Image 1 (cartoon, rainbow, N blue to C red):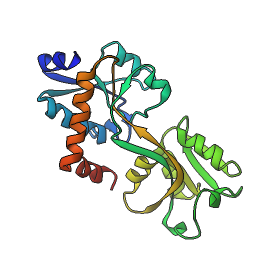
Image 2 (tube, one colour):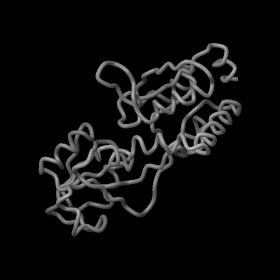
Image 3 (cartoon, rainbow, N blue to C red):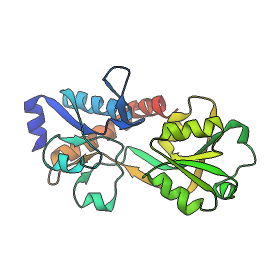
Length: 229
């Protein structure tokens, strides 16, 4: 099993996309930081081993997992049917739903999605994300502005070039640092789990028991309230 390989090697090689705030990213000087990062350190403390983050492209992070470049994937990965065909997921540690970020000035007169389905409304999204899809299917009449990252869209909604922005709930919760304000959309959400290789119940159940215990003692709630307010 990979578990024995880890406890023998003495290090937990964690594969991640070091550019997916606030789950995993770089700091002022090369080091790693994020929710999944602290979680990775916690699991590495559970194993009793050191931590080694292996930065990999989001596109080729699953084949890298399957080729044994690292033992586990922790990068806010969404559990999808297409991915469960390739890799096994652990039990959900985070729930990412669709959330709109707006200015505090517009805290009133805004109920839900349909309140922004006007053609004079300007919303911003990150290109290629599910937030873009949600902004398409639920806000078609409004102008859609796509950007490289969520920070640029956030700048656009803060400055005034955008009435709102559409992003994931953890991201929107993170950017609340407070000036703007958060509105959640009621429909459905997405599960987030860690990813390991096929045919390894030992590591899987270890991860699940460790997560269960971290939710049982309350450490997970501490780490959750730390990052997502």
